[PDB]
Image 1 (cartoon, rainbow, N blue to C red):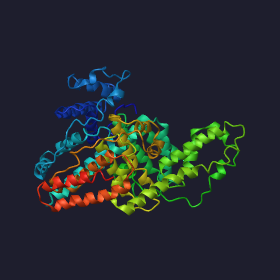
Image 2 (spheres, rainbow, N blue to C red):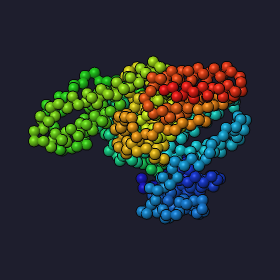
Image 3 (tube, rainbow, N blue to C red):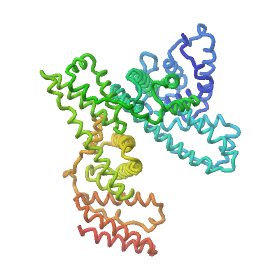
Image 4 (spheres, one colour):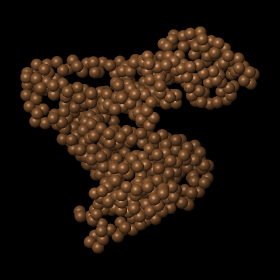
Amino acid sequence: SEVAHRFKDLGEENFKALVLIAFAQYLQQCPFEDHVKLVNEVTEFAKTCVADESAENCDKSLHTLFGDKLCTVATLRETYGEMADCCAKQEPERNECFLQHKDDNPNLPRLVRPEVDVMCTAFHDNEETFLKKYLYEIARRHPYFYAPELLFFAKRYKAAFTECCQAADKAACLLPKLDELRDEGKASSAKQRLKCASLQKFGERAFKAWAVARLSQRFPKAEFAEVSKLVTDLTKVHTECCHGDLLECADDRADLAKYICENQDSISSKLKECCEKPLLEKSHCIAEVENDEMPADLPSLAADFVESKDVCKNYAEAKDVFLGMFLYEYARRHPDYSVVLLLRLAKTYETTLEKCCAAADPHECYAKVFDEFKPLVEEPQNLIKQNCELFEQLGEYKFQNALLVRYTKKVPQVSTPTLVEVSRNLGKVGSKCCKHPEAKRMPCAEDYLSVVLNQLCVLHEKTPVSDRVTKCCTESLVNRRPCFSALEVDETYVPKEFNAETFTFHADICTLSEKERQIKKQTALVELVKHKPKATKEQLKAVMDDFAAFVEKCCKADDKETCFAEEGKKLVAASQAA
């Protein structure tokens, strides 16, 4: 096992795909015919490394080889500025600036989709060149996308594209497949961006606590040792795949799939059918599985940590192992609880217990600790129940209207389309999981909503305008949502002056599509409510009703903007009646 580059475990066909995405992930050079001969020269380098070792220099580090072989590519300084700092050797490495040297750069405008015949013929003659073109096309938009998932999308692309040219269906055979592949790629790119961003920001202990809470919730039938080995190997895979070294990432995911499909008896009872799959299907199928059933007999954990007097000696012997025992025993029993709430309860437990061992008499200090968990769980169930019944009462468009009229008085200095996009995404989250029962509502409420808040945080991080929004972003991830939800109104906002030309419209608004009419409607609504900062919402509902009736009155009218001159005149005549 002295070989430093064993691609024979991966195979020759899989080796060429994983180096092209790494070259797209290291630089964004728009010619790519040199990328094919780059793949060819590194695979003949690999074929010379096959079966003889002492005659060559194949006993080197692969990250050093990514350092040195990229210098021969980067010879043009005005197009490749990655040689500006150093030559990127092993010990003076600059991978820590190569990670964000081109990250979040949408340099390409858009991808076009022509008619079915041209790439049907390109699939008919140049199919592997079309697949390389698709990997080069999708590898330039999101650079922090999960590298064992691209082979799954390429296999699904080949399987969904090998039958549409043969069958009579051409547009409808592939177009919703392309739409759902783009939507699944956007969702998985957002999830991988959130996970690698949390690993880059909040250390490693928070990632280990989050993953032991999730693995305690998913697999309840296992003991602590298999959970500890699984969380150590998953922490290793995610700390060495959001960084580079993609070959080790794919091989480590492969042996984790081998270990989880070879020791399935003591861990779970539902993935026995899931392990009867191909290898890429085995890698994808494990990450979305149903959680198992509860154990039949389980005692209360109040008997283990209250009347047991000798618990601080176990805490002084081991801290994080003892908190791992407490978090595993608390998250095995409650499947409806969110992971963020469980991390809040574990943090409250450790900051109570490190104060209670500071006292002289610790057994009277932790006599009442389970009363403090009642207001930490009494709030968000009532909040989710109240907003879910508001969605069940008013309907979805009025729910989006209510969430846009509610948050506009909290932070009234943020711009228009950021507010419109955040209110429409929270309307989608509120319409997503009120069709579920009460047990399956909290992970919807703390899973879909966490993408929208850090999306808003990285949108406000580029252009900082407010201060209390950025103050909530600088805290920990376990208290970001109560930092946002405990905001009140501000009295420091100046009332905006009266515009006269944006309240009026044009008579082709009925010719627009309904989504564009809605974007115009909440645009004029958010300008209308930022004109009047006073809490006069009891008149605003009737004003909204006669405004909607009086804009559909002019839809029946055909005066060709003459009725629209009398429309906005009566609206600004009725504007002062407040």
